[PDB]
Image (cartoon, rainbow over all chains, first blue to last red; front, side, top):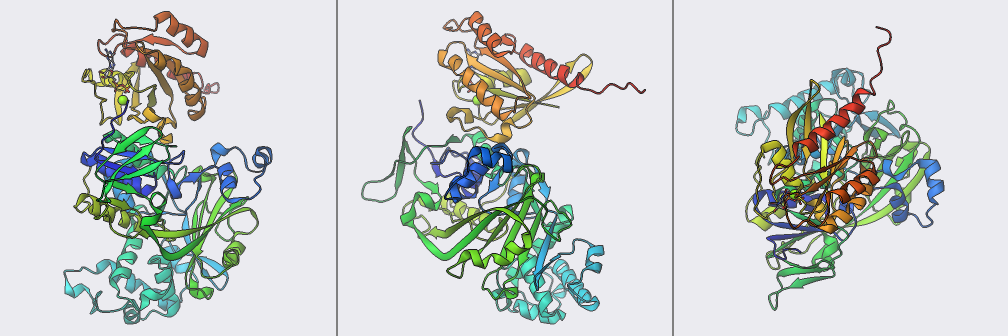
Length: 441
Length: 175
Ligand SMILES: Nc1nc2c(ncn2[C@@H]2O[C@H](COP(=O)(O)OP(=O)(O)O)[C@@H](O)[C@H]2O)c(=O)[nH]1
Ligand SMILES: [Mg+2]
């Protein structure tokens, strides 16, 4: 039978929790990691196709119908929340330092396309594509090139590299003016490289936009043709990998084990333990996602529409690419928020041979989400089936000093994992009392 | 390169067998050994130098929470029970079923009765072969503590796997 005392109890096996669990176990703590659901991943789990029907459709089709049309569930691993990995991002820097690269294989994403006047254009990957792209005239490209030289050459501690600009005092629009960049170029650099979901960054200081733009460029440099990576067999592999890191170093894992009751300490309100069908387990603190403590969570105001579309064919005007990101900036549609599309396919063992997965997502701003995404649906051509779903974005009410209930944030509508790792670094400090400094294993 | 797995109930001695084979060590300490991800060891098969890549379950079998990446691309799978614990024997049929789903029927299996040194035995060597024969896979009775037929486990499995690789090579009839 089982130890009941742990240094840390972690609830739910989403990527945020799993990364925390792994790092804590590596640190020497004794983690117990429980999940009410019968599988790894939480809200960002990759699920089979039948499960996709069970989750999002009103009248699921027969096994027999599904299988002739789409094939057997073991070929399908479909992300519930679309994300990519910045090549030089922080999640990959964690993957490397923790050696979880051993439990996950990556392909490069084929490219990034940006939307204009109803047509998608490829973001240039090298000089040949730069030269032949019709997004910028000859001389705009030069200024653009002089701008990008500045992003690399800029060194914080050498004023002579700044070209007369201060990232704290100048706005990004003021930086853009300095280099002579017209508004189309601003949109390009802002929505396609810095990856902002609206134009508010223009009036805000430059610093954060600079950093994000430097990250893009650094991510394209590392392996080449694009800034993104994607795990074979779906995003679900990421949490599983960290779960193993945790297990290797001492962690205990229970799935399909609902939390019958949370236990708080007498008078104090702080966390004591939890009560499961496998007995009762105690720890001085708990790390959990918002579905385990709804009352200690508040909405952030945002709701996100997520549309999963199965195609029989490559996306139009993408040179038959195997993977793809489409950015539809808001200015092009009269919105407050960009629309995103992520495409992956049988090349990543996420669906049966011949199919393509296209996951459209955006922040809802009307009372009819299905209509908001229509411009994106037109880009895909013939769609075989749509799985629609809305999710509300929660965050913790307090930081967990009062109660030792340290909650994670819901996964947001950004295209990559940079913000998720920001949540991890944060939650780590709140729990440990120390910054997350990275050790090589 | 060969990906080898060791599967079975907690407590049967999977991590000891692995550590004995690679390092030539046994830790009696009643604890689980933690800290093991995979070991590497070169084996010699009929002149051919074959590297075995041996992956530990890291205790995830304890509540049936084994990661998919563990199973993927496994060429050999050692199923292990404790000869002193009848339940670990009964459950082998269940492990067999599971492994054959996840390894996708391409892996070569092998049954191992561990802790053959103990006098508190409750499963005979003959019982173990009955089940091994029933499932279509070879049988070895081992002790990680005393080094009883531990090497034979890994050589037997490596040899069967190379047999299948070698008989699937296209013949150069041309030259
Ligand atoms: N007597 C004896 N004890 C063993 C043998 N192998 C393992 N053990 C003991 O049984 C326990 C289980 O060890 P472990 O390898 O972690 O089991 P696992 O759950 O299958 O990985 C440990 O306390 C070992 O010392 C063996 O061949 N003989
Ligand atoms: Mg073990």
